[PDB]
Image (tube, coloured by chain):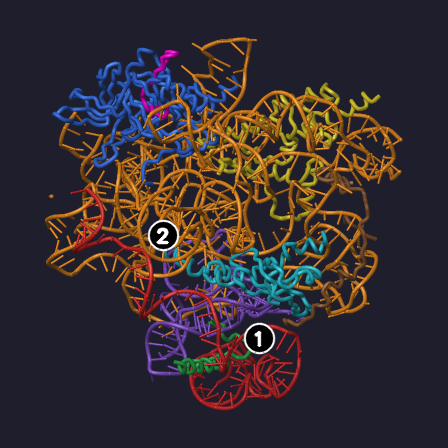
Chain colours: A blue, B cyan, C brown, D yellow, E green, F red, G purple, H orange
Amino acid sequence: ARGPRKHLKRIAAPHHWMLDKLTGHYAPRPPGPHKLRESAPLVVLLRNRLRYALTYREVMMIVMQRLIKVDNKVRTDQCYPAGFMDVISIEKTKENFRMLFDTKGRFVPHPIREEEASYKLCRVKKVVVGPKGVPALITHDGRTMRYPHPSIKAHDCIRLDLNTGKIVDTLKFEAGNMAMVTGGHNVGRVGVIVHRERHLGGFDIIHLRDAKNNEFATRISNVFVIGKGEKAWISLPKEKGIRLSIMENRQVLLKKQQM
Amino acid sequence: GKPNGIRTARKLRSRRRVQKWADKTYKKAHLGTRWKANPFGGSSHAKGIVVEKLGIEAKQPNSAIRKCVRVQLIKNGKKITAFVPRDGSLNYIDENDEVLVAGFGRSGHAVGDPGVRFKVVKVAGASLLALFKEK
Amino acid sequence: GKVHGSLARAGKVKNQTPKVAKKEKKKPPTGRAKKRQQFNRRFTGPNAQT
Amino acid sequence: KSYRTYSKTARSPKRPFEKERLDQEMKLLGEYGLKNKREVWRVQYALAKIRSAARELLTLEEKDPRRVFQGTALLRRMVRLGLLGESEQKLDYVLGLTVAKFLERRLQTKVFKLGLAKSIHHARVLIRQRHIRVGKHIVDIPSFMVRVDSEKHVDYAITSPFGGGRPGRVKRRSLKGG
Amino acid sequence: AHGASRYKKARAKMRWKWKKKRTRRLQRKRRKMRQRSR
RNA sequence: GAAGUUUUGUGAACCUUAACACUUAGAGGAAGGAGAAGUCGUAACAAGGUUUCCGUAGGUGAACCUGCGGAAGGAUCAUU
RNA sequence: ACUUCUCCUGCACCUUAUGAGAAACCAAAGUCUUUGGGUUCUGGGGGGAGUAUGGUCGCAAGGCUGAAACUUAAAGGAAUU
RNA sequence: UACUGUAAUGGACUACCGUGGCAGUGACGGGUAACGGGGAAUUAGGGUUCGAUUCCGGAGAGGGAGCCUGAGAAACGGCUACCACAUCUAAGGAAGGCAGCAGGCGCGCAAAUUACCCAAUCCUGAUUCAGGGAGGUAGUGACAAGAAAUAACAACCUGGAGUGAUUGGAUGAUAGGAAUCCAAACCCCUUUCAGAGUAACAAUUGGAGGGCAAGUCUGGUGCCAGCAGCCGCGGUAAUUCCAGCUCCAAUAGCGUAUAUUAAAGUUGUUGCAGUUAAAAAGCUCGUAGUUGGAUUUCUGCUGGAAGGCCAAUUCUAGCAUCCUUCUGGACUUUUACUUUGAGAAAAUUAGAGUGUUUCAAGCAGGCUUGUCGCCUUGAAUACUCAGCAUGGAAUAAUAAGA
């Protein structure tokens, strides 16, 4: 009541962080570009994915060196919400991490090449006219690129340059274009787009087809266009967003563990 | 018989809530009279002071004098007669001595050989078994 | 019941009866070792007085 | 307050006193050398988890994707645990299990089966007195239950007199005393 | 209450017709006594 | 821009009356059950010695009795 | 009017059931653990009690609705000797 | 209708104006030993009872009311007032709010230390550094859950493997170190000098007429004392009392009391009963309510894609006269129903994987003289009436009647 809540609790955290039940009563709380449940804070990358830090203390000792950057910019706050399709860049080690969705429905820092780690994609939420009658995009990231093409519509991605501010490569939202899912049940799945239903009132949905010919649906808010009909602007994680079945995921896992 | 048809939820649902009250055990639960009735407050045990030492006789066939105690609950000062279990122990009570009262195990009602629903579990906190045993 | 039943005889037979001590005997086994003995003596009524 | 789950391993039967029941339980104590009737009811309860799992699965359909997944996982346990033999992998066979199958698999018997212990009772005392290496590390507890690849592996602990160590304490008192 | 059994008289009893009348005289009296205290 | 002040609204608190709710005293009256054995009958159970019972009405120490119309749960499944 | 024969609709009756029931008995009390044609009302051990209080109908007598405290291990059904 | 007011919409409020709104499908009022939900207990299925309490909302800071500051409060570890309690006063006055953490009084059947620290987990700040009774560690703790000591083996009478204190030699309970753990102690896990022979380091708690497993035993008592959940024992021989001996049941637990669930097909949708046992309104009309007869493109042959198994089973195009406006949606009366799909927090629950020594648990681990370590490591998945969407030929409502 009475104002914004400064604590978040463990358990009442998101499940896709995979913070454990014991070993803490509270969990780190991420406001930044991204939402609370559609992001992951910079602490649980460093300690609970990348395994650089042990403790919450040690993440302060890393981040206040000014070694961590995101989007070619130094972020000093340890609880910064670093979300979908943000680049992370550490100068020592000289390795870069683009955050994608894993096929199971988790965040994972996908390691990438140095030339690839310049650019990143931003799907545009809407397009809107600012003052002096100038046009302007706005993104899922909460950037606002201005003077686009007239070409560029809602619900489609743009390759940003990052080294400079400006856009470079557009993409369109149509049938036969590659598209990852960012939320809901089918998260972490990439497939070409077959068809979308309108439903003139609320909630457009899209059916789309995995590269092993599995068909599945999501709302348009969740869908995020990568690239053209086959091929893709970005590098993909392990499995490339197929999501193999429950008995298959059993068989591959226990076949691994026997060595 | 019953109404079977798909839209007969009201008649089925209304008939249970009405005719649940025909049970004897349902009324003892769900009426408001449970809280006024009993000397206990819907409770397992209750302390009180022994106003008087009393003797009552079992109904035939059994004949004898059973040795019970009249007590006033501390919370309500309501008089009750509590039976004293085992041989003797009457000497142990002492008028004006606090005694724990427990249910006879029959949910009020009555026990065996008249009109007594309680048993004195402890005297001065010592308890009856320890003394009879002498342990 | 009548209230005026007398309380003089209370503790008759507890006071009447002759006292006698328990005999000292060797202790029984307990737990698993008890269930060993009970197994054997059945399969190679249980209380039969003279 | 604390986030720790917990459960009950056993539960008592509905009838306290039946001469049919008490005789057949007393045989299982006498064969396998058990402390009390809780140790039977533990395994009675542990079977009924596995049995009620198979009872749920077996009603459905052999081509159903729930049964083919959850059945094959359940059959892997019974092969691993050495409870069902590998020649029959049918889910139906799990139903034909008994308490004697579980109680032959625990470490009281598998010591005795091994034969080092000599007698059922002795085998329990050898387990609790810190002998008998199962695999790499020693095991203190009768109700262990062995996973069939591990069964050849049971041997006296490296430490201890049977094993080849200091001879406890009482042999030293005789040896140094003399 | 009693309803249909009302007068079953399975075992030695007062007799229902008489019993109903006896209670009516008790009840009738209750009225005038309760109206007297108004 | 202070103290003080005008008129509004927000409005605690206290009081009068009334109603509703819940405990609680009461001379006397009149129920039910319990005793454990008393006094007076004998009503019912057999055609229980006037068959039993119902509804209603009146009367009498008490069970009960009688009038009118019913029932067999009757003591008759039955005779121009 | 009567005789012989068929049809529905009545009050019943006799005989019998691998139909039912605790049994007495039952063409319904059958087709109900091989349990679902449709629907209205009522009952949950025996008393206390068809009482108390409140309501409502009645000119009254009383009718309809209708409790509790406490009490009790049996009340009750059909056949057998 | 038109102001006003608000962060904005509104009878939210004010002027005039109309006479409406809700209700037998339960309005209005009363009771709750009522905060709601995620959930918990309960061994077929269907259910019944509980949910103050780990998370998410809500409300409150003795009772009500008012208000400042600020992005945000009608805030109480902020202020003003009254009421109810209560502290100091030199008697003029002043200050108080533990339903925060300990602690005490009082109520009760009923509940712990006035302890140590920010090391972990997170939060606030001008912030790498300061602070935190949030939180964590220890003490009390048979509320509870898990594991399992109280012996084992020999040689030396019953003989068809058990007994027999007859001797006999072969691990921790305990007490103190070592290192480890810890913010600092402590416990666990390791290894250590001592450490059991009536293994005195001695297992108890309820029973022994029936239900209920287990003595027509032996003393004392004599309808007494007492037992007895129910039926029943006791009046001078007690298979039930008070003892002793022996045996039974569960066992580091077991008995009792209250509430609750199953048993209860004794609340009955699945699933009871109503001639005589409890119970068919004295009898007809009747509005809701519930339930409602038959009937409207069925059959046949030729493909196509799949398909289990040594052609069946799915789905689908044609042709028997079968739309079209275009290049997927519009029309087919409308829903219910069923199917698939979306979206819906975790914890708990079921459940995949994994030797926490087993186990309750936990979410970890596992390989390996290799060093930018690897398994491009794991932590799956299900579950969550009404609402949104969709394929469909029956069934049932409902509509109609160029």
Rendered location of residue H246, percent (x, y): 79, 48
Q: Count residues near mark 1 (Cα–Cα under 10 Å), then give few for <14, some for 14-19, many for 20+.
A: few
Among the 4 quarters of the image, the one containing residue F1: top left
Q: Can residue D76 be seen from the camera position used here?
A: yes
Asked if B119 appears above or below G61 in the picture, the reply is: above
Q: Is residue B39 magenta?
A: no
- Which element carries disc 1, helix, strand or loop? loop
Name the residue nearer the viewer: B16 or H125.
H125
Residue on which the image places disc 2: B6
The Cα–Cα distance between marks 1 and 2, rounded to whole angstroms, is 48 Å
Amino acid of disc 1:
Arg
**Could you tell me which residue is drawn at 26 percent across and 18 percent down?**
A228
**Residue A250 versus residue H306: which sits nearer the camera?**
A250
What is the span of residues highlighted in magenta in the rendered image? Answer: A77-96
The answer to whether H49 is drawn above or below residue A23 in the figure is below
Q: Is residue A205 above or below residue B55?
A: above
- Classed neighbour count for the residue bearing mark 2: other residues with Cα under 10 Å, few (<14), some (14–19), many (≥20): few
Relative side of H402 to D138, left or right: left
Mark 1 and mark 2 in contact? Answer it, CB < 8 Å. no
- A127 with respect to D166 (left or right): left
Rendered image: mark on residue A143: none
Badge 1 sits on which subunit? E
Front-lying residue, H109 or A124: H109
Q: Position of residue H98 (x, y in %)?
A: 44, 46
| Residue positioned 49% across, 35% down in the render | D3
Tell me the SS state at disc 2.
Answer: loop
Residue H389 screen position, x and y as percent? 27, 37
Within the image, what quadrant is residue A6 found in?
top left
